[PDB]
Amino acid sequence: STGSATTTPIDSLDDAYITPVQIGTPAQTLNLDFDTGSSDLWVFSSETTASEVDGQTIYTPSKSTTAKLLSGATWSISYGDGSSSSGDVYTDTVSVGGLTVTGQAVESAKKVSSSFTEDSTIDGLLGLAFSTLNTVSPTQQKTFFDNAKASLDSPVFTADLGYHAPGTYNFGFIDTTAYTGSITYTAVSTKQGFWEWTSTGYAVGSGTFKSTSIDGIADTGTTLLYLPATVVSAYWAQVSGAKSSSSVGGYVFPCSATLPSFTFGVGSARIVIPGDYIDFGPISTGSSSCFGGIQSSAGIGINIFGDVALKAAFVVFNGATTPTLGFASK
Ligand SMILES: CNCc1ccc(Oc2cccnc2)o1
Image (cartoon, rainbow, N blue to C red; front, top):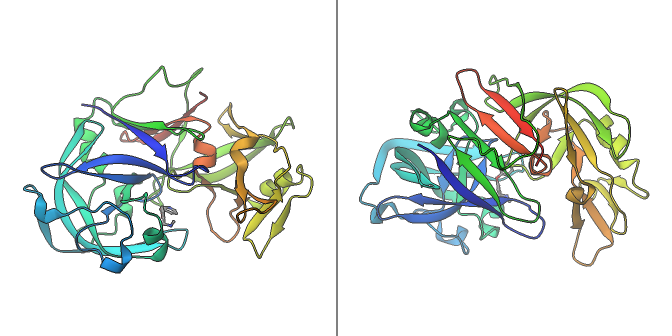
């Protein structure tokens, strides 16, 4: 079997992408943030604190004839951005782009932090990292991919994120019409539960390529590209007026600037992020100060290849017995 679903930017800045997911019988369709940096499928629900819901579509397990309480299971998660949520767990039928999983753990939110409440376009998350990160206790649960893997024609999923445009998540097959040239595969470490790999280097604009190993994770649930301070300094030094601002929270630059591209290495191959992809607009409405799409990972403890980087490629998450990551231009 296979699945194919369209993923859509939640706003003008591609701050995140939402994908429709069918849950229960009859289907309840919720727009979920597919996150390869986490491993919980959680949703706004009929159980979520009333004052913490503001515009979101909710999952009502009591309206689903195939929902079953997973007795005594609870979950609690916190993300790299400071947000968090928690609640209880049902199993139900979950379908993504025509691909169906029965008995999927659907983690129902009792509580969500203010940033979740504040975003009416995201109805929850669907984790696609390794199941060892799943937060359900006392019985840890499997991600959707993991549950589906057996059924798939090939044990893979692919992320084809758009720049200011819809993209696609495919399950169980590689669409050879979706990328240019060939796919370069690279080794993955599963030891931290992430799709963790090692980039071979970088270039700033038309600059010479710097060969250097940069460990990082492929994280569709993170908006920006977070890299070592050396790398990031080297990038912003090419932008007149760019500065790191502690009051703002990172690098900002003149909104009048034209940004240089950023190239990252995948083995012997190169993925080029166009400069426009690195522009995240005014730090505040009307401001002439713009927020950068490449930021320091110093203080995160890990480098993150977030949407800014992934959307410049066709990315293959290969969940074979020995997982690997593939990158192609498109
Ligand atoms: C806006 N804060 C809540 C929110 C929206 C999407 C996500 O999910 C995240 C955020 C950061 C890292 N990984 C996943 O949280």
